[PDB]
Amino acid sequence: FDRDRLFNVVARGNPEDLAGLLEYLRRTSKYLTDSEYTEGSTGKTCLMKAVLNLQDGVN
Image (cartoon, rainbow, N blue to C red; front, side):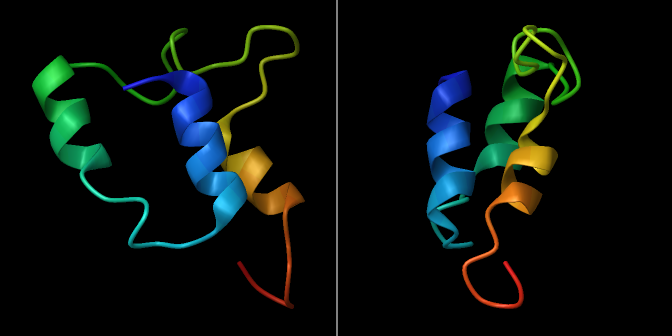
């Protein structure tokens, strides 16, 4: 799994594409707020990236 992998998934916007993130996260024992999944340039997370992409009125 990768950081920009999850960024590409949340940029895409399909929820079925966001599959097994919980299983992978519980297997790796790491949180989404941990430094591997932070950007680190500004601290930007995946949630803010998904909010920045609103194709329709929702994502």
